[PDB]
Length: 162
Ligand SMILES: [Cl-]
Ligand SMILES: [Cl-]
Ligand SMILES: [Xe]
Ligand SMILES: [Xe]
Ligand SMILES: [Xe]
Image 1 (cartoon, rainbow, N blue to C red):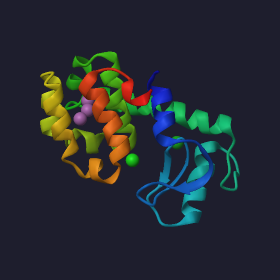
Image 2: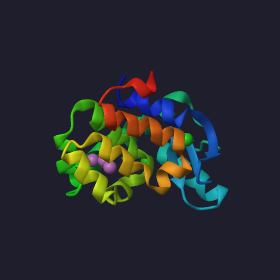
Image 3: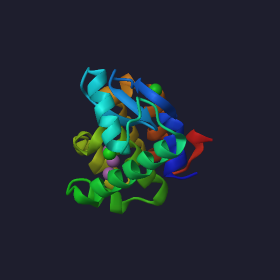
Image 4: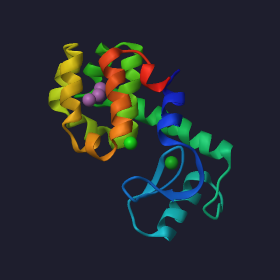
């Protein structure tokens, strides 16, 4: 298992514009197009991201390309964030994938706000971190996904995804 397969399981794959769990227009493997309630706005953003007139529909290869760009951007964002980088660098490979999934889902600002859990992770207090991460709007809104990510930080194995 790796970060790509992990995220492909959590995000699914959809070739037509769809609304995500928060009701925002998205396409592909969780690629958020806009927070705007406007379908046309989402369609304009899609065409711009793909480089053609897609008419709200893309191919699998195009979805995979947006996904590659999005994973890369997510990791790079962590390395560029002063509150995140030190935590991420202290983690093992498995746990780093869990950090990346959270960032892909909620953005780096969002993750950088889990101050207390960040500290627990950095000190390798796994069970404690797991309990603190669950006290969040993130966990109450997407509990199955949050549980899988949380168990990954807690155990450092891919069991939740097998
Ligand atoms: Cl883009
Ligand atoms: Cl869920
Ligand atoms: Xe992190
Ligand atoms: Xe994190
Ligand atoms: Xe976190």
